[PDB]
Image (cartoon, rainbow, N blue to C red):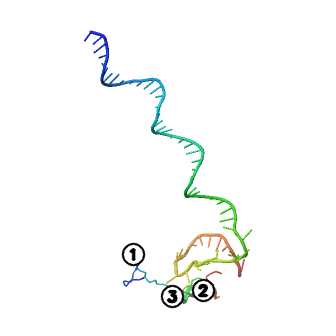
Amino acid sequence: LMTNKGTFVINGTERVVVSQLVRSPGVYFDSSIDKTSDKDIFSAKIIPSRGAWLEMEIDKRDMVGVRIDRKR
DNA sequence: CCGGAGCGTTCAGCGTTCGTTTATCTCCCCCTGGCACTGTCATCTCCGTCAGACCGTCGCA
């Protein structure tokens, strides 16, 4: 239990469980520039709270492709 | 005026007690072997390095 002071008294010692900054689950779209390609490349990713992640990179060599956990 | 008795010290007969062993008797530890309805493919990893190089590898040309 947390006391009225906001602390956990565990093993006779006073601890605090701080909040954690993380990325919010959802879709995320990014744009980048490659010197070799001389063109812009866009990417999308769907990061969940618990499950696996999937990505979609468009026009690496003017083809759009999917990354299912970056396997093949 | 030596002589004897009492006293001090020092050894040989057998008589008991120790110092160190030995095999037998309980209690425990430790390893190999038995179980007979059937039961025949797990497991979660890993992401918001990072920075570029070194290198071999590999399919396209």
Whether residue A32 is visible: yes
User: Do discs 2 and 3 share a chain?
Assistant: yes
Q: Is residue B51 left or right of residue B38?
A: left
- The numbered dot on residue A54 is 2
Between A44 and B43, the one nearer to me in the picture: B43
- Residue A29: give x, y in percent of width and height: 55, 90
User: Do discs 1 and 2 share a chain?
Assistant: yes
- Residue A24: give x, y in percent of width and height: 51, 88
**Of discs 1 and 2, which sits in the foreground?**
1
- SS assignment at label 1: strand
User: Do discs 3 and 1 share a chain?
Assistant: yes
Q: Amino acid at mark 3?
A: Ser
- SS assignment at label 3: loop
Between A59 and B20, the one nearer to me in the picture: B20
Q: Pinpoint the chain carrying mark 1.
A: A
- The numbered dot on residue A33 is none
In the rendered image, which quarter contains the C terminus of chain A?
bottom right
Q: Pinpoint the chain carrying mark 3.
A: A
- Residue A54: give x, y in percent of width and height: 60, 86
Mark 2: few/some/many CA within 10 Å (<14, 14-19, 20+) = some
Distance between mark 3 and mark 1 Cα atoms: 33 Å
**Of discs 3 and 1, which sits in the foreground?**
1
Circles 3, 1 touching at the beta carbon (< 8 Å):
no
Quadrant position of residue B36:
bottom right
Q: Which residue is mark 3?
A: A24
The correct choice, above or below, for B29 with respect to A57 in the image is above
Q: Which residue is mark 1?
A: A13
Q: Amino acid at mark 2?
A: Leu
- SS assignment at label 2: strand
Circles 1, 2 touching at the beta carbon (< 8 Å):
no
